Amino acid sequence: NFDKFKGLFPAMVTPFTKDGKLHKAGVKEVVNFLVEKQKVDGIYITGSTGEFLLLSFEDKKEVMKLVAEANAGRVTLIAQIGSLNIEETKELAKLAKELKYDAISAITPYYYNFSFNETHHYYEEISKAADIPMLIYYLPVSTDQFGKLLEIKNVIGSKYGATDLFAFERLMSKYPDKLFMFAWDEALAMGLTMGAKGFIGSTYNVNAKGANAIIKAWEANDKEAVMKLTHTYNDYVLDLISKGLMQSLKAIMRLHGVDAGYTRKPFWRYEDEEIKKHAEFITDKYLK
Amino acid sequence: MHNFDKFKGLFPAMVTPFTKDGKLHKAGVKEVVNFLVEKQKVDGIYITGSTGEFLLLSFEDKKEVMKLVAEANAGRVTLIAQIGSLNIEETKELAKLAKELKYDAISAITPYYYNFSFNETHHYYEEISKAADIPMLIYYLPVSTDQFGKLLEIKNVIGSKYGATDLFAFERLMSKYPDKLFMFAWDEALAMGLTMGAKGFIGSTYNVNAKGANAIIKAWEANDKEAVMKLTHTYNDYVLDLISKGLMQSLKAIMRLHGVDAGYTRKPFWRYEDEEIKKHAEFITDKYLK
Amino acid sequence: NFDKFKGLFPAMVTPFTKDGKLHKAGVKEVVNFLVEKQKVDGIYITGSTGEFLLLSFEDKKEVMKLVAEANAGRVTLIAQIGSLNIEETKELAKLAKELKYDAISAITPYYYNFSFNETHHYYEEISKAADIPMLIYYLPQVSTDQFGKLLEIKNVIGSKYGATDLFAFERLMSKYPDKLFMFAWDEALAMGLTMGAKGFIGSTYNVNAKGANAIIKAWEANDKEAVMKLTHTYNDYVLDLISKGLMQSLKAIMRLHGVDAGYTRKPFWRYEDEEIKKHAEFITDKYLK
Amino acid sequence: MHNFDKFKGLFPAMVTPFTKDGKLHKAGVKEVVNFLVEKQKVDGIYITGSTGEFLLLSFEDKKEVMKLVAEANAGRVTLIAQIGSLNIEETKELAKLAKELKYDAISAITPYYYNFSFNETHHYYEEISKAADIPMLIYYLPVSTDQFGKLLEIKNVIGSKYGATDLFAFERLMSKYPDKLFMFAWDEALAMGLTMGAKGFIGSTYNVNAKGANAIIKAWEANDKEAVMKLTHTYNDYVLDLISKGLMQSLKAIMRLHGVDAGYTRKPFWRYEDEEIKKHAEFITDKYLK
Ligand SMILES: [Cl-]
Ligand SMILES: [Cl-]
Ligand SMILES: [Cl-]
Ligand SMILES: [Cl-]
Ligand SMILES: [Cl-]
Ligand SMILES: [Cl-]
Ligand SMILES: [Cl-]
Ligand SMILES: [Cl-]
C-alpha cells in the first residue's frame, strides 16, 4: 500500500511576505517548483521546516488548500497537522481527508514533558477524527513501547528523524509492515541500507537532484558512487546551514525565480546582500 | 543592597482554571487569586507561565486571564505576567496590556521548539522591550555568565527567572550581576537559593504549600539552621509526593479539595479519574498541608 | 595499501583461571579458535574486551608474546597498548614492533578529563617509541578538523572508530581518504560498509564471525535485502548476548566449544555455573549452530 | 548518633609530590603534610585520591605514600586514605595497611572505565570490607536514594564522599541517612553543603586556600548571611582562576612558591614551563592567599 510513499519528499517551506503575512501566491509557486523543477515524489507540508508553529489555524488550513490545488494530484502529499491544540488538529485531519491528502503526520506533543500515556492518548484522539493514514513522529523509549503507538487506528508508520540508526534498525526489524519515512537527510544512504524507501527532509527543497543521485547509485549497486555522492551531499548540507536553514532555502528559491518569500519572526532576517550571496554560493557549488 | 523589595518572597506560578470541557473558567481565575492571596498568604503571583498552561491558551484567553487576575488581586500582591510565545506581535500586545493593567513586571520564555541562536533570542527580547515601559524578566538560558549579560542589559530587563538545577551558574550570576534581580525558580533548592542571595521565589509548588516554603524562609531569616534543613527535607518529600501524579492536575485537585473552583487541565494533559486524583489531593493535603 | 586490515577483527578476550591468574595456554587456544573456527581476518588484543586494565604490565607482555606465537603469522595482529602509564605503553609499542604486530592502538587517556594538548602529547610520546603503525581512538570531545591534528602525528595511520555517531564517521571518511578507519560498532556493521569501512573491530566477532561475515558477503554481492535480514539477526544476537555480562558470555561460549577461555577477573561479576552455561547454550543454539 | 567529630572541617585532597623526572618524591610527601597541618591548619588530610594522582602511582608508591603521611602527621590531624582501584587484591592490602597505620578512615572510588553494574559495585565494596575493620567512605554513584543505601549498609561503611554537582540528591541523602557521615566534596558549593548539613569537606582547593574556605564556614556558623555570599563569590573566583591552568600543576606550583618541596605532576598531565606556572602561582597567591 506504500509505493506512493517511495522517494523524495521535501519538507516544504511556507512563504511569508517580508512583513510576515502568509504569502498565498508564493505557496503555489513553491509547489510548482518542487513538482516541476526539483521533480520530487511527494511534498511534506506544514512541518518544522514549514514554520508551522508560526502559522495561525487559518494559515494552516489555507496552506493545505493551496498545496492541494497547486499539486492537482501530481505528487503524493503528506500534511503535518499536530500542535498542542487537539481540537484544531482534529479539524486539520478532516480537512486533509477532504483535500485528498495521502497521509497526515503529527509531531510529538512538545514543550512540556508529556508522558507516554499522554502521547498515546493524543494520537488516539487524532485518529478518531478522519479515516486517513497517520505517520507518528519517532519518540526516543523501547522498540516494544513504540509499537503501542504504531498499533493505533489509522497509524501506518512513523516519520523517523532521529540520529540513532540502531533504534531505526530495530524498528525496521520489528515492524516490517509499517512505513518508516526516513527524515535524517545526512544519513540518506544509511537509511536506504536498512530498508528505508521514502525520505522527508528540508534539504530536498532545493537539491532533490543530489539526493536522487545517491538513491540511484544505491539501486544500481555503485558502492563507491553512494559514498562519493553522500560526501558531496553532506558537504552541501553543512554549507547550506552556515546560515539559517529556512532563510537559505527560501533565498535559493528566490534566486531561481520562485516567489518563496521570507521566514517569520523570531527567525533571523538577514541583510539582502548577505543572504543572496549565500544562495549564489550554494547554487554555484552544488545545484547546477 | 536591598533592591527589588516588591519582588521578595513567594510567587506561586498560578494554575489557569479550565472547565471539564476545556473552556477558560473565568470565575475560577478569581477564586484561585483569592485563595493564593488570602489563604496561601503569598507575596506575589506569576501568571500564564508553564504551570498556567500558557501554550494551551488562545490570545484572547491570555488577555482575559491577565484582566481577571488584576481585577481579583486589586493591588494586594505583586503581579508578574509571563507573556512570551513564538508570536512576537501578540507578545507585544500582551506587554502593553500588562502595562495598562499595572502589572509589576512581565517575563517571556526563551523562544522554544526550534534551536534559536543567541542573536535570534537577543532580538526577540529587544522587540518585546520596545512595546511597553514595564520591567522584564528574561528566562535563564544555559552561553557563559558573560554572554547572558548581553540579554540582561536589554532595555527594561531588570533580571531573570532562574529555573535551572545548576547552582554554580546561579552563584556565578549573583556574583557578576548584583544589580539585576534573579527570581529563583527551583522549588526543591529554595534554601540553596537563599544561601546565595535569592530573595524571591517563583514556583508551581507554592500554589498549595506556601506555608511550608515560608517556614523554610522564616527559619533561614531567624538563623535556625537546623530547621532550615528539617523543613527542606519535609518540603522536598512534599514535592516528590505531589508530582507522583501530573503536576497541574494535582495542584488543581488540591485546590478543588479546599473549596476553590480551580477546574481542570486542558488537553493533552492526562485527565485522571475523579476519585483517583481526589485521593491524591487528600494524600498530599493530610500529609503536608494541615 | 591497507589490504591486510580488511575484514573481521575480534577484540580478543584474555583467559584467566577461576582464581584470577593469566591462563597462558588458554590465550593460545583462543587465538587458534579465532583463526581456525571463526576464520577471522585479524585479532585485536588487550583492548577493553580483553580486560586490559585488569592486566599487570608483565601480563600484557606475556599475552602479546603468546598471541604472536599462536598466530604463527596467519592473521593480522593489532595490540591495544594504551594506559595512563606512558613509560609502560612505550615499552609495549617496542614489544609489538619486535613481535611484528601489524599495528598498535592506544585508548584516549582516561579517568581524568585530559585536554586536547595532553592527548596530543600522549600520542606524540608513544609515536617516538617504535616505528609501527598506530590507530588512535576516536574522541568526540572535537571537530573533524582538530581530530586531524591527532591523525597527522608520526606513525598514525588512522583511527579505531567506535562511536555511535555515523555522521562524524561519514565526515572522517570524506576528509581523510588516505587514513584507515577501523569500524568498531558491531551493531552498525552494514552502515559502516555503506560509508566505506572495510575493517571491523569488535567484541561480538569472537563467537559470531560467521554471522558478521554473512552481512559483509551479502553487501559485496549486492544482496541488499539479505544485508537487512542478516543485520536484524546479527543485532538480535548482540542484544541476546549481552543479557548477561559480555566477557563472561563470550568466555562461556568459547568454553562450551571446548576452548580453555577461562574466566573474567574481578571486579567483573562471576556467574553461577549453571546460569552462564545455560546462557552460552542458548546463544549457541539460537545463532551459532 | 555516632561521634564523627574528628571528620568535621577541612580535608585537602593531598597532592602527591613527584620529581621532575617522575619518581615519587618521598621527602616532599612529608613537607606537604607539614604545610597542610601547620600552615593551612587543616582538620584532616585525604590522601591518594584523584588529586593525589593515584592512578599514576604504583602499588608500592601507594604503600609508601600512606606510610610517609602517617609518619609525618604523627596523629596531629585526621587521616583518610583513598585506596580503591580495579585491582581488588591490592585494594584489600591497602585497607589492611591503612588500619595498621591507624588511618581514621578509608575510601574507595567507584569501579571505573567500564560500566559496572550495581551488583558488581556492591560486591566490590563487600570484598574491601572483609579486609580490615576500618571505617569506609564509599564514593557517591549517580542511582536512586534507596539503592545507594544498600551500599551504605555494607559492613564498616560509615557514609560516603559526595562529589556530585547534584545538590538535590545530596539533600535526599541527608534526609534519608542522618546517622551516616557525608563528606562534602564539591568545593564550589561549600556553603550550600553546610546549609544542608555537611560538616566535613574534602577538596583539592583546600590544599592552598584553607583560610578562604574556613572564612566561609566561620561566617556561616556566625549567621553572617551576607559574608557567606561575598566569601563564596571570592572563593569561587579563586577556584576558576586556579584551574585556568592544570589543577595539580597549579597546586604544586603554589606550594613550591611557599618553599614546600611539592614537586611536579606525572605524565600524561601537562608540564608547564617553570616561569609560566610560577607566575600563575604568584597571581593566585597575591590575589587570594595573603
Ligand atoms: Cl520538517
Ligand atoms: Cl533572510
Ligand atoms: Cl511556571
Ligand atoms: Cl485530572
Ligand atoms: Cl575492545
Ligand atoms: Cl562467569
Ligand atoms: Cl580527590
Ligand atoms: Cl607544571
Image (cartoon, coloured by chain):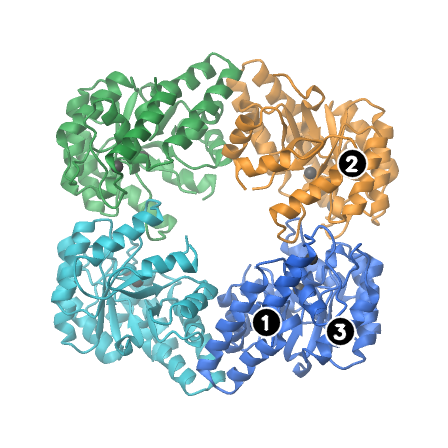
Chain colours: A blue, B orange, C cyan, D green
Q: Mark 2 packing: few (<14 Cα in 10 Å), some, or many (20+)?
A: some
Q: Are marks 3 and 2 on the same chain?
A: no
Q: Secondary structure at mark 1?
A: helix
Do residues under tags 3 and 1 come within 8 Å of each other at their CB atoms? no
Q: Chain of mark 3?
A: A
How many angstroms separate mark 2 from mark 1 (CA)?
Answer: 65 Å
Question: Is mark 3 in CB contact (under 8 Å) with mark 2?
Answer: no
Image quadrant in which you'd find residue A49: bottom right
Q: CA distance from mark 3 to mark 2?
A: 52 Å
For residue A31, the mark is: 3
Quadrant of residue C148 in the image?
Answer: bottom left
Q: Is residue C20 visible?
A: no
> Would you place residue C127 above or below residue B23 in this image?
below
Marks 2 and 1: same chain? Answer: no
In the rendered image, residue D198, in percent from the top left (x then y), is placed at 42, 25
Whole-percent x and y of residue D28?
Answer: 17, 28
On the picture, is D200 further left or further right than C59?
A: right
Q: Residue A99: image x %, image y %?
A: 83, 74
Amino acid type for the residue under numbered disc 3: Val
- Looking at the rendered structure, the secondary structure element under dot 2 is helix
Which residue shows up at 68% across the image and 26% down it? Answer: B10
Which residue is more in the foreground, C228 or B75? B75
> Which of the numbered marks, if any, corresponds to residue A284?
1
Whether residue A89 is visible: yes
Q: Which residue was labeled with disc 2? A: B256
Q: Which quarter shows the C terminus of chain A?
A: bottom right
The picture places residue C86, in percent across and down from the top left corner, at 20, 50
